[PDB]
Length: 109
View 1 (cartoon, rainbow, N blue to C red):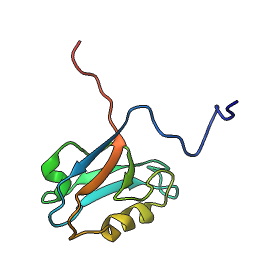
View 2: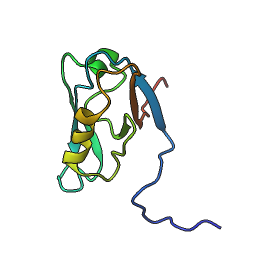
View 3: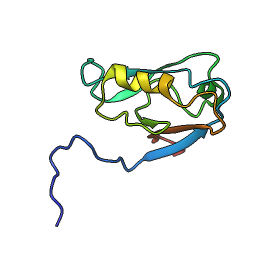
């Protein structure tokens, strides 16, 4: 059957949500954590820079756990890497920004 449980490096989350942010100038998003950093190994939104693509979206916020941007991996990655991807992303292209993270919170009742 299936083997694992206890603990694992990679494993898609149940509340894993994926959205898209209208790309115009560039990502303009900050990340936190890093297998080397203290906030890691998980990666989260350090802060939404005022004047970015996501900034306008709002869907995302500072503190949310990221998963992958554009088409890379943010889970269990190097703080510099995740950040290196944003600026390395397509940028100034035609397709929007592929944002993947986990969404889940108390709503109503």
